[PDB]
Amino acid sequence: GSHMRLDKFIAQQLGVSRAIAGREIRGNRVTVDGEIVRNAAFKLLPEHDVAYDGNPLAQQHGPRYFMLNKPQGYVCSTDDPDHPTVLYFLDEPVAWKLHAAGRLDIDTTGLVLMTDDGQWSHRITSPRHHCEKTYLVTLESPVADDTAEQFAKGVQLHNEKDLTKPAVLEVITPTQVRLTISEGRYHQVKRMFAAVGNHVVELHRERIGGITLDADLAPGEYRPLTEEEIASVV
Ligand SMILES: O=c1ccn([C@@H]2O[C@H](COP(=O)(O)O)[C@@H](O)[C@H]2O)c(=O)[nH]1
Image (cartoon, protein in one colour):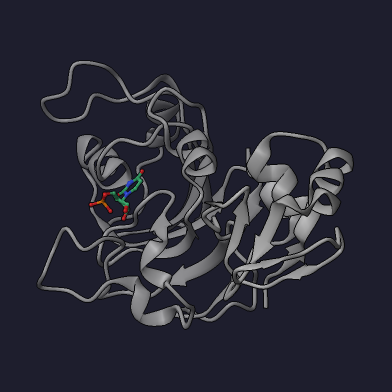
């Protein structure tokens, strides 16, 4: 249903104040659907076609953010053509414009922030940026008692130069543990338990920075992000 005041739009598009945008409007210099609009409060709907001094001001759709609970057997990109993308779950216009701010492997489930906001996304995904992801990891063999520390100090991924930046591991059950990592390498958790001689059976992402997965968002389900959620991300 997204829409906005015509002035607020001319404002954003021109890099001027809404107060001045309003002015330019009464100056008979703003057009909608090929007609002169002198009202600053005009309700600008997507199907409209705005123009400034004859020049068409491309309607840059507002940005969207969504919380998804990724189910198994689906991927977060089209890089692979053997599995359907998680887009099969987003009933939204031009959904294809959305990208996962942090992809989840085909059989990993949990919080996946679908967004078409490049700036926002990058700040969450940059390899240089400290962002905390917290997973619920199910293990083949009871977590080794000395694993805990090993993760805090750090482990060396098989054939990797550096060490995994300190991670805190909590023990829910002998074989189920919650893991928090501020990094984001490729298949990092799986390989981490690899180094310490264990195997990841299941893997669920609960948190990304300041956004946590709702307790009642069934896998496959999603929902727009809350104003606070956007601003708080990390
Ligand atoms: O510590 C981590 C973080 C992520 N992943 C998994 O690795 C993936 C990233 O690779 P890709 O989804 O871009 O192919 C995440 O999707 C998730 O399933 C892990 O095994 N360990």
